[PDB]
Length: 233
Length: 206
Ligand SMILES: NCc1ccc(CNC(=O)c2csc3nc[nH]c(=O)c23)cc1
Ligand SMILES: NCc1ccc(CNC(=O)c2csc3nc[nH]c(=O)c23)cc1
Image 1 (cartoon, chains in turn green, blue):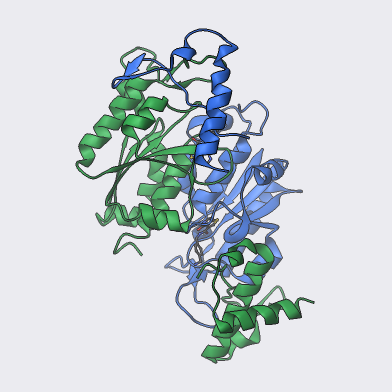
Image 2: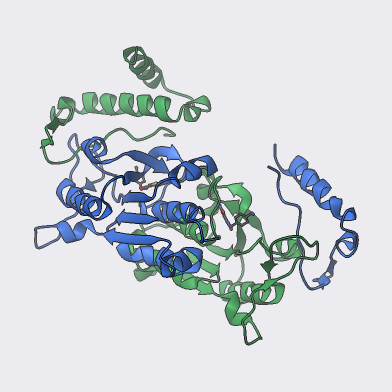
């Protein structure tokens, strides 16, 4: 997979390319991430990357020429078929279904914005889609772009339902006097699977009940969920 | 604000400490971020940071001893009143109300998990709260921790309900597309912004 990035802080992307799972994907030529900075496309001594809005009022926008030229250089490096994504606080909110869709692309271009955003005409002429990583305010699109890279990289071959995970335990047998649930030491696989499934259903119900609303459950899951609910009283 | 971080990849945090608004906050002593790596708390030649789950199944967990010792060193650096946060897919899903609450803390300790996560008993013995950044799967807690730092840093003094109306800057004509004529005249007449914000919202989402 090839990923082009437009950012005023391209060195932030070393957090992705030099470390962990994405870092090993880069070293093994399974993932390639290339960055271009609009500041490097400026013509003036002050390397001006912002510009005033026609409307008026407060806030600046990214200057069109340096940003458009950087996007064009990423498009020329990408070649045919790259999808251009603008990371925006008001774009489509990312979820696992969204990640799965984005991961079908062999080539992506991720545009990070700063200030109040980008000119509407650049969205119409250079952007394919707009995406957000959640309903919270950040200083820019760099952390969202890196989050998107990490999520999609998991889908690349060679790099590596709907319920929260069950509790997990490892050594020691006694941690600050607290013991591991005996079923996990029993060697009874079906009892362990049913205990973990019941815990997963209970944790989903107590912490994130909305996740159960749009979820078809098996007879076993329905039976185990009712059991945990009854024991909760 | 002081933030302690537990991570197997502490160098990832330079993306926060060396650049942009958080980088500026660090340079002006408004924000301090200190990192400890569980690998530095290992006793064996192979610096083993993972361990096998009881009950089997695929996946490994973070080894308890190196992780617990690293958390303890961050707690000793923090002193009284630090809130310990585990970045977890099973945690409270972050939103702006959540950021506002987290931002009231002068001291945080952010614990980043790798592999399938951490021992449930470490959550009871060490963790104050669990937080997620969204309903998507990542390779670790580091990008969520950095996202949390950036969001809360906006609340530090000295650092800084509708869909937006479209905005325009130079040039007047871009790829044959002109700026709406309204945007070059009357201040009150520009109430076309308020209408476009409503018109965009009605057409996009509710
Ligand atoms: N005044 C409106 C305004 C404008 C820009 C910004 C800067 N933020 C981003 O560029 C951003 C990109 S994707 C994303 N996903 C979640 N949260 C975010 O903030 C983001 C914040 C708020
Ligand atoms: N199979 C269980 C499992 C365990 C760990 C991980 C690694 N992920 C995290 O540690 C994480 C922390 S906060 C967050 N917020 C959104 N998404 C995330 O993945 C995260 C993924 C899946």
